Image (spheres, coloured by chain):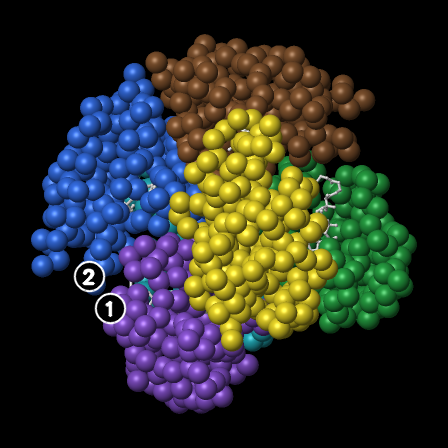
Chain colours: A blue, B brown, C purple, D yellow, E cyan, F green
């Protein structure tokens, strides 16, 4: 029974994230999206709002489930009987940074990490940049799933 | 049901490669190692030699097989009913180059690519560098599987 | 009637920035320097002031403060090009995403120029940090800014 | 009377190149595409030909072959700007050295533009390699080049 | 006669750092480890603790001494009659950032910087990441010298 | 007695190289410039011509000597009782490539590598680009030492 965990804050989930979810779900028997809460940086959406937006956007992925998590990511992964993390990468800079975390995670817990390259169309999309653009009235509707931009309107007003 | 292809020239396979094979075999139901041959440029080892060296050092991986091929990698993958490539990466430079190839491969054939970070211990190991060092008498024993080391020194002499 | 906008915080403006201004003014009929009001050592007005003195010899350049989306600043003045300097591959990877976002949302393009070799290590932040602990940044900043920097720390 | 030169081997010209041509023509009064005669699949004349057909709708652009120093090509036509597309940070680091060399020896500046996201993975060499082994590169090349590519391999 | 300064916050020193100290001490007549303190932001360990942890794990290096400092690194270096900084680097990203600092340091004070590549085994080790992993219960024992591990777990509790 | 080897083809030596030589000679009791011959790529200048140009350019560095070398670099270094290599770096890309060679050299022979950042003024200078520019009539006189550009005129005519 194969599987992997896709970690992130997803505040909010973007089409870049969604593309990674779809690609992981096509290759693993199960995927768990882990919505990670930092009590320092309270973002725009609550953890429940983020989970709901991810579930709506992944409605057609039957082997994908979404949960919140806290603490050590590798503990979250092992607690669920898995030992793989899947993450999207956009740049070589991203790779150099994630490489250190991947090696640390494999060292401390034997959990592996599989990376996928961003889809070309979403290479410049990030939750943070989309929010910043939207805050000043930019149209990011083509960068976010449908279930998100509606809720994003509400938060900005 | 789930599966991946691990491609390369493997001339010869290194411990860096074997680490990637082992990690792929742990996460996918089957792995096929694709020894890709350019029919116009010969390398150091024959196809038979390349395949034998990989088989000898992967005997403990029951769900891994080894095959040679040529032409487009995505055709090799799809012909076998698979849809995933797994590749190791050492550097950000590697990632930027492989990103292009992975995006092209997804574009023309819908085949996805999963990258894994090199094991720290083997981060500087490459077939080409190991051959070059060995050519001038350097000690590469701890970098190559036993199935490879004496076959390499044999070629060199 | 070509034109480009050179955006930044410019706190203060360095010779590195000035070099980009000069090169942009040489290739576009009109250049506007956009001081984006956001950290901070100088007032937006002093920044603008400091840029204005360093740029006296450039007839087709002017300096304006800005708020909100950079692409709105650019389009509201009838332009659709941004010119920015780059020092490193890391800079490029970061800037590429903003460039692509800006083109996507507003059709504003971005042209990058390589740093002058002499100014490869110059940044507003590093120049401040070094001047803070008494280091000589004279050769890195416009004469204009150099005095106002010494007096801002004294 | 602004202007820029877009240099390359263009063998063949890709939609990635075309996108840069379009963006350069939008910001400079005059753009010259320089086909530098140096590997090779198409003749310099076909390359030039193939670029000319893809660029019909751009009135301020022309296509010329070139030999020797790029900066001499640029200056001999009265210009001192080069426009080139960049995909990656690795590209930038390589191109930065040539940009700085070109500025040093001839005072010719270089403006870089970020690849369009859709064409991030498109290169002349990769498109050829894939078309060689039967892959469909239709959506990546101009309709002009696409037929001449199919007939060049058949 | 020849000498170098190895600077850092060392909060705490890691095996990655100690590897750099050892390699510097092998190549220069003397090495001074400079524990640079920001008087406005405290870290996890006091200056006394930082110095003690480094001394305890460098006892076998007769030509290495440890001192704290603050303000400009180049003043610390020149005051001691030296003219060289030695720093470890892990990534190309690190190199691009440190290049700027090294060129500035040479510009303002004529002080040169020599970089050394990280040991492969410690390529993913950083004080900050080790603290973060330890904070959430991860096993960082093989990444830190013995002089550090129990002092860190003590702080955390 | 401290020391390091500065390897390269130096065909011809540039001011970028010279800057590295000067900086190594300021920090090590002795520096050996190793002019490495590849029988495949016969460059523009013979090995003796290159050594002569380097000696003339380093005339004021009394602790620097110049020799030709072949074979494994780490053997060259150890044969002369040293165990350090000094190399200049221009870019993060250069660092990622040299990092692998440095780790390999330390693995196979215990020889370390110290890198220095390029001087800002010479960041875009390389022997290959200077030759290419000069070949088509570009003025590279400000990029090369005096003892070189004269000989470079002769070779081009
Ligand atoms: N356009 C895109 N394509 C592919 N992957 C992407 C992507 N945008 C983001 N990702 C990936 O999705 C991960 C999770 O995204 P987010 O949750 O929004 C960032 P975060 O980890 O919560 O905060 P951070 O910025 O401090 O790292 C990122 O770390 C990145 O790996
Ligand atoms: N030390 C290492 N750790 C992890 N992966 C490695 C590795 N060394 C090589 N690899 C991977 O193994 C792949 C195949 O290596 P080789 O067969 O030796 C040369 P290649 O097949 O021509 O690779 P390339 O053309 O994709 O660059 C590399 O592309 C790289 O992805
Ligand atoms: N030495 C240099 N040469 C060429 N361009 C430079 C340069 N230094 C900076 N620039 C460019 O000019 C822009 C403006 O820089 P500044 O606004 O003064 C500081 P900043 O790095 O932008 O702050 P930030 O990182 O917090 O956003 C930079 O973002 C960069 O694009
Ligand atoms: N997808 C893309 N988007 C934007 N610009 C691109 C691009 N692909 C290529 N370019 C730019 O257009 C230039 C011309 O490329 P080409 O001449 O066709 C192949 P090349 O990479 O230059 O060959 P070479 O590497 O052997 O020198 C590239 O050097 C690059 O600067
Ligand atoms: N695993 C490793 N291998 C080699 N060198 C390392 C290393 N980890 C850290 N270093 C080096 O040791 C230096 C000091 O590390 P630390 O004191 O922990 C944070 P720092 O002092 O704030 O570094 P920085 O500000 O220069 O980025 C780093 O700058 C880096 O050069
Ligand atoms: N401008 C510069 N500043 C600092 N260091 C430089 C430099 N130009 C070159 N170097 C360094 O000097 C070394 C030797 O230079 P060269 O001998 O000319 C290259 P090479 O190793 O002979 O051939 P190669 O290009 O196949 O690597 C380079 O590997 C590089 O480390
Ligand atoms: C949330 C994240 C995955 C951030 O990485 P990301 O930016 O790729 O999403 C990382 O911070 C994390 O793993 N948090 C859980 C705590 C942890 O395991 N830290 C140690 C990572 S080596
Ligand atoms: C280009 C490459 C060397 C890379 O794959 P490999 O290093 O794993 O063998 C080659 O073997 C391959 O993957 N396929 C053969 C030609 C091809 O597939 N070209 C399209 C790459 S997008
Ligand atoms: C100010 C700046 C240009 C960054 O400039 P800087 O790198 O000089 O700090 C960028 O942060 C910006 O555009 N701010 C205005 C708000 C905006 O346009 N956000 C969307 C960026 S895609
Ligand atoms: C042709 C090109 C622009 C490279 O273009 P390309 O990346 O598209 O192949 C470059 O090789 C060139 O300028 N050739 C002409 C000779 C020259 O100018 N050499 C000095 C470069 S600094
Ligand atoms: C910026 C830095 C953190 C880097 O040095 P460090 O990481 O080795 O401690 C700092 O401690 C330092 O080197 N000096 C203190 C301020 C300074 O020197 N600024 C000038 C750097 S060019
Ligand atoms: C000549 C050089 C130093 C090239 O590196 P460089 O480009 O930095 O000069 C390298 O090829 C070399 O070391 N040649 C000697 C043979 C050798 O030792 N090869 C193994 C290097 S790990």
Secondary structure beneath label 1: loop
Query: Circles 2 and 1: CB distance less than 8 Å?
Result: yes
Residue E88, image x, y percentages:
54, 52
Q: Residue F156 or F104: which is nearer the viewer?
A: F156
Q: Quadrant of the N terminus of chain A?
A: top left
Q: Which residue is mark 1?
A: C68
Inspect this view and state whether residue B111 appears.
yes
Q: Is residue D31 above or below residue D127?
A: below
- Pointer 1 chain: C
Left or right of C120, for residue B25: left
User: On screen, F37 above or below B128?
Assistant: below
Q: Position of residue A153 (x, y in %)?
A: 12, 53
Quadrant where the image shows the C terminus of chain A: bottom left
Which element carries disc 2, helix, strand or loop?
loop
**Residue sitting at x 51%, y 73%:** D2
On whether ligand 9 comes within 8 Å of the CB at mark 1, the answer is: yes
Q: Label 1: few (<14), some or many (≥20) within 10 Å? A: some
Task: Write down the residue under mark 2.
Answer: A137
The answer to whether residue A104 shows anywhere in this view is: no
- Is F154 above or below relative to C42? above
């Amino acid at each position: 029974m194969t599987g992997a965990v896709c970690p992130g804050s997803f505040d909010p989930v973007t089409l870049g994230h969604l593309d990674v979810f779809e690609r992981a779900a096509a290759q693993f028997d199960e995927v768990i999206v882990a919505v990670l809460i930092n009590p320092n940086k309270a973002g725009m959406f609550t953890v429940d709002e983020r989970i709901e937006m991810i579930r709506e956007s992944t409605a057609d992925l039957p082997n994908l489930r979404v949960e919140s998590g806290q603490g050590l990511l590798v503990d979250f992964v092992r607690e669920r009987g898995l030992n793989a993390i899947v993450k999207g990468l956009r740049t070589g800079t991203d790779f150099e940074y994630e490489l250190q975390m991947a090696q640390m995670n494999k060292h401390i817990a034997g959990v592996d990490t599989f990376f996928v390259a961003t889809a070309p169309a979403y290479s410049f999309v990030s939750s943070s940049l989309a929010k910043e653009v939207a805050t000043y009235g930019g149209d990011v509707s083509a960068l976010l799933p449908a279930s998100v931009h509606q809720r994003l309107l509400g938060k900005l007003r």
